[PDB]
Length: 30
Image 1 (cartoon, rainbow, N blue to C red):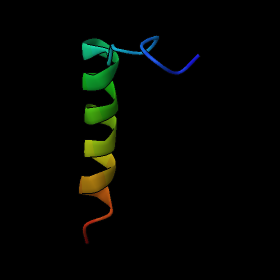
Image 2 (image 1 turned 135 degrees about the vertical axis):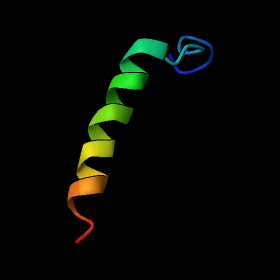
Image 3 (image 1 turned 30 degrees about the vertical axis):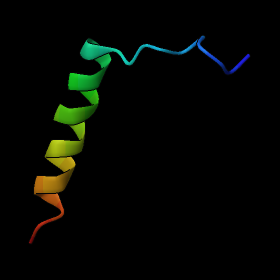
């Protein structure tokens, strides 16, 4: 269901999506 079966976020996997999106945000900037 979609009521309270997702009250989490993920601290680790989060820092991973941040470091990755960072390198791409620094390579697209001329």
